[PDB]
Amino acid sequence: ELLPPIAHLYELPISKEASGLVHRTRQEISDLVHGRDKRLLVIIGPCSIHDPKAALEYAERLLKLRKQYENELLIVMRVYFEKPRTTVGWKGLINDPHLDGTFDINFGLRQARSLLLSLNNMGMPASTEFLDMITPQYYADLISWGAIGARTTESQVHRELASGLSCPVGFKNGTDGNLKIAIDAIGAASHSHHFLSVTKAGHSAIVHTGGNPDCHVILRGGKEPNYDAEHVSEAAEQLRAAGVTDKLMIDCSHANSRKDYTRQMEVAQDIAAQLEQDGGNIMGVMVESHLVEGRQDKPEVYGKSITDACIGWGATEELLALLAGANKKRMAR
Amino acid sequence: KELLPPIAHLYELPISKEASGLVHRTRQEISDLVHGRDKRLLVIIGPCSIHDPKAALEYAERLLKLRKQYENELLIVMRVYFEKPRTTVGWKGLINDPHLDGTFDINFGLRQARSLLLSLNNMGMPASTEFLDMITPQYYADLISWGAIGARTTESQVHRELASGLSCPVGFKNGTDGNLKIAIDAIGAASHSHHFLSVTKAGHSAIVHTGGNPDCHVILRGGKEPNYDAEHVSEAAEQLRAAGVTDKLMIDCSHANSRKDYTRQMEVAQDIAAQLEQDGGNIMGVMVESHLVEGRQDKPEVYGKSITDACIGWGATEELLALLAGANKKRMARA
Amino acid sequence: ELLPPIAHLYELPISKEASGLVHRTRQEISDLVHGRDKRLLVIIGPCSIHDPKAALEYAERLLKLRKQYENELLIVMRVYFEKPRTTVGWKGLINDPHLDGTFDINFGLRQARSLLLSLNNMGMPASTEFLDMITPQYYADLISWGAIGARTTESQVHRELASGLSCPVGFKNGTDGNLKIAIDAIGAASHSHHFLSVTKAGHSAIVHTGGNPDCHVILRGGKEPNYDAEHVSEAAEQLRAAGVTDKLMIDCSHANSRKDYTRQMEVAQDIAAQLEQDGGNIMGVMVESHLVEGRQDKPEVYGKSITDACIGWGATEELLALLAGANKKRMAR
Amino acid sequence: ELLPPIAHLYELPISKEASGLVHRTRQEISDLVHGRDKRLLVIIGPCSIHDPKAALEYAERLLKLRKQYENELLIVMRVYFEKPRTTVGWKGLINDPHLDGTFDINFGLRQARSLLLSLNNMGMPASTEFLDMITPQYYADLISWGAIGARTTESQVHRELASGLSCPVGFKNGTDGNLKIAIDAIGAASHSHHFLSVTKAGHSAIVHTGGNPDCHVILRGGKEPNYDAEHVSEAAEQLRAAGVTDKLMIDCSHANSRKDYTRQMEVAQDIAAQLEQDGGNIMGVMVESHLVEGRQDKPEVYGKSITDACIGWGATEELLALLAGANKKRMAR
Ligand SMILES: C[C@@H](OP(=O)(O)O)C(=O)O
Ligand SMILES: C[C@@H](OP(=O)(O)O)C(=O)O
Ligand SMILES: C[C@@H](OP(=O)(O)O)C(=O)O
Ligand SMILES: C[C@@H](OP(=O)(O)O)C(=O)O
Ligand SMILES: [Mn+2]
Ligand SMILES: [Mn+2]
Ligand SMILES: [Mn+2]
Ligand SMILES: [Mn+2]
């Protein structure tokens, strides 16, 4: 039997501090999307959250770097609770929190909210993919940035969802490399929509959104990678032709690394060189990072991904130092 | 704004014994085609979108006569699409904006969609639609004999979840650039059990556990290039078999297979007819965008003329159906 | 499965005319409760509604008398949908509309609302006993006056309900004759309350009422009748002592007639004589009247009560003429 | 915004032990109602719960006596959360838990449920008056016996409620002494009913109850006390005439003590003498008892009532010893 959002909000109401951090980070990201600030948004952290203890530890380490590089980078943790699978498989902490096929969704929603509240309380803003239609009412108040995934960017129900979110949103190119669907999606999500959604009390209702003015695209590769200067330039052209923001984000992982976590640093190096040359159209980067590198089928090892493989903490330190130094030069130019 | 729950609509428009029987029977018949147990050709045919119930009922009456006439060769089911996925923005269909004026009277739209579907089934004409929205199906799905998941949503996990709990057979379209694998993947996904959030007949969110949908198949609807010919059908059947799913598929004559030109649908149908006459063992169905009047219009001025994708008119519809019936009659007679 | 009030409001929205009639009649009745007009409120009609056809016919006849006597009497029809039984039995049209133990409550609510909308549209305002806690959301917008019954006047949940109704409300003395519980009830219902109630969407909620300033008592007999001058005078004294309105209503039926419908006219005569001597504390009277007199266990005869016995239409004409003539004299003096 | 029962059941699910205690105690009480066991049910404790700490302390003391007298008495604590007032006033812990007019009903429901869970977990079954229509879904699973108050026994909505409760229920005579309304109420509540109620998910619904076969009357005084042998005998006769159980309960407080807490022991003495002569029609007694005697308008003193005045702990020990000794003799016959 499904508890409504108000039951979770009652137990875990947003704090003054978390509320402030969310508000501020959304504004800061909006400034990047619209070219008002030349800091680099960095969406970085696990492919998926499957353990809160490891997540909190990761966050504590990330926070020290968030502060250290705050003049160059705007660091925000990946806190992904919903995973789109190719066919079937574990869909994330919300859907199956005990990792055993019990689908204890009430527990999963409580735990997702609790983790997000602790993260924001310690000073670390959070990001997630918004995949499911009804779950956002449980946690979206704690989210500073949202993704719509490659598999759902062309979906009208996701563009509707995005049009009503209060955080900035990045739309990914399609899994085969189609960018136009993401440009289209900004067009769609920036407008007003009417559609059915569920209230905080757990009731279906008609909602009328105002449109989301803070949307941008994400280059995450296709049949070929799309992270280099030539692809970025092509994309900026099309963005301008559609009359939407020509500031974009580049995912170092997924199809840009060819699913090989060791190649994320390669992509980051290319981005660093672009930032040093010019890189005027880059407002952000995405990175799949955990305490420990690689991946595992069963959750045996602490801080090691059970979905896409990630770089470990050591490489994370290097990647962030690399991007901070490069962007410091861009910002000084 | 104040959304009525499905039970309010079910109270005013409860399913009849006859409509319930027609739906049950047609779903079974279509399942038999999906699994190669019958060699009749499923034909999903009708308007791109429903925007007028009067014209829809008139179209249905004409179609019914041909449904009966060709019932040994073709299993004809009307396109009764209430939900339209747009490229960017635009009219999303009768449910979202029934008065066609930007008033978004969704309660009226749901009532009217249900009423039309009940009348169609009561006159003997089964209905099909694209299932796009997550919450609307509880209002009408009991009256639907076949569902589409669109090219733009086939790769979407929430649509595969939805499909996994529907009681009707479901066709998954290849992606707008031509990717077939996402539709094969989608059958894999939708045929399994899922747990997810959905809304009850009382209008309350709830956890649902579906049993998986065993009646799913792919639809070839074109990409950067058309994919309707024998070479593409054969390639697709191979992949289907490699994934261990049904290698019987449907071919859309419209959208990217006609290159968005309604006058080319007949071309595609002719190619399918020739395939059915040579062999065509992997074809179980075809889709066609048809209305009383051909073409399209921005405003709903002309009666029975599409306000979304352009359609063939009634005359060409008669020819197209006769062409497919004759061709499939030969297939069904062949040893 | 229970439809929420919004489903019924969607099918049967209140009209401009019915809205106006309700608003006006509530104001008019308030004027009587607070001694600003000396017309006599007359709550008259069947013990219970069991047939809408007969109800509409009765209403059409009553309307003619409502117009005729409008300078002396303010006539409002008894349209009672909810009946409190001594032990068990038929609870009214809402609970069991088909009169067969099928309890088709959705149909009953729809039919109760439809009838009330037609009555108001033809110019006849309606009254009912408010017995059930959740049903009022379905029809209260069409009610000009409400009763809380003898069996429920001492009940805190009914006093809460009354405190939030937008129509004037009469509280009946207890079945053994206790008047204090009704005086207490005005005290209670005139104040603000917080309690649980159900919304128009069918969801439980906390409500905060403002108190009902239009409440008054009804004398309906006990072990003995309480309709005479001596009892009216005693009651007015106690009313003043409790600092509440000393204008009251007298029921000609139930324990004041000793459950004998032929004695209602006796009571009405006594009231008429009071109105002619003085009768300053009387603002209303209640009468159980139908097309045909008496009662019946099965609904075999048209327009004949299946609950308490009623006077027939001929005696109804006489009773109303008697009260109109008596009050015309009161008003002139 | 009102949380639904499932939110509270999620945080405070019933335990194996509490569930067992509730189940056993209901059965044991049923056996007393139907004359299958001659132990005396004793409903004893505060007029109202306003403090959980004091309530838990009281319960710990009462538990020791519950064990000590378990062969003679079946002791169950008064854990009343809902109070019917004469006009206006504090309605109990649920309605206004902070005792300040803030009406924090969500907090009140949570706290009521938490207290009941702790009481049952320590071995002490609980009783309450069921006054409100929607609150029972939050706690009734933890209640071993329920009262319908003197002010609501004649109310059809309370008789409906009772008909669907899973615990035995006592109906009180009316505030002026009318017993027939309580006999009528057993008749009503023992039958099946259809009516509107709210589900564990907080939605209104139609419910079909099976009737409550475990109902009985409670003599709690009227204009005069009704606790003596004469009154008990008169009541048993009427009970038998109505074909319902002629085993009844006697309230030592309220109108039987003439609202004087010191007189409760007097009433208990009379009952003891009855149990020693014969007393075959007595199955229970009710007593208003707290840690400290008397009452207070403000909650200044610990363990002292803020509603009706109670006897203190010392007199409680004497009263219970008196009833145990008397009933031990009855049981031995
Ligand atoms: C879901 C995946 O992103 P994408 O949509 O680019 O495949 C991820 O970030 O883990
Ligand atoms: C929505 C469209 O289908 P497709 O998903 O192939 O674009 C249609 O049937 O009008
Ligand atoms: C229920 C009855 O009134 P009372 O509450 O005085 O018995 C009636 O009006 O039919
Ligand atoms: C409410 C009161 O009992 P009664 O209903 O007899 O007044 C009590 O037990 O506190
Ligand atoms: Mn990933
Ligand atoms: Mn189309
Ligand atoms: Mn009556
Ligand atoms: Mn008390």
Image (tube, coloured by chain):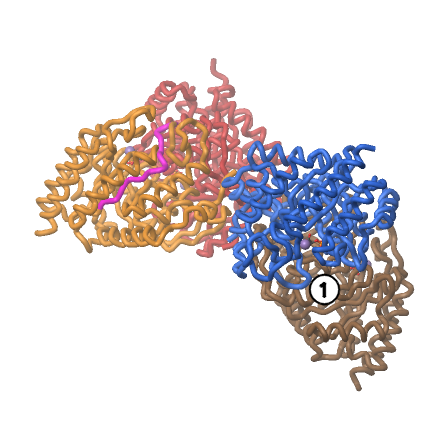
Chain colours: A orange, B red, C brown, D blue
Q: Does label 1 point to a residue whose CB lies under 8 Å from ligand 3?
A: no
Relative horizontal placement of residue A190, taking residue B145 as reference (left or right): left
Look at the image and give the residue range highlighted in magenta.
A75-88
Question: Residue C181 falls in which quadrant of the image?
Answer: bottom right
- Judged from the image, the secondary structure of the residue bearing numbered disc 1 is strand
Q: In the depicted view, which residue is nearer to us: D202 or A61? A: A61
Q: Chain of mark 1?
A: C
Residue C170 is drawn in which quadrant?
bottom right
* In the image, residue B294 above or below residue B64: below
Horizontally, residue B259 falls left or right of residue B126, namely: left
B313 over A96 or under it: above or below = below
Q: Amino acid at mark 1?
A: Ala
Dominant secondary structure of the residues highlighted in magenta in the image: loop
The quadrant in which residue C322 appears is: bottom right
The percent position of residue D193, horizontal first and vertical second, equals 73, 44
Q: Residue at x 58, y 59 (%)?
A: C194
Of residues A291 and D316, the one drawn nearer to the viewer in this rendering? D316
Residue linked to disc 1: C126
Which residue, as the protein is rendered here, is positioned at the far top?
B335
In the foreground, B116 or D183: D183
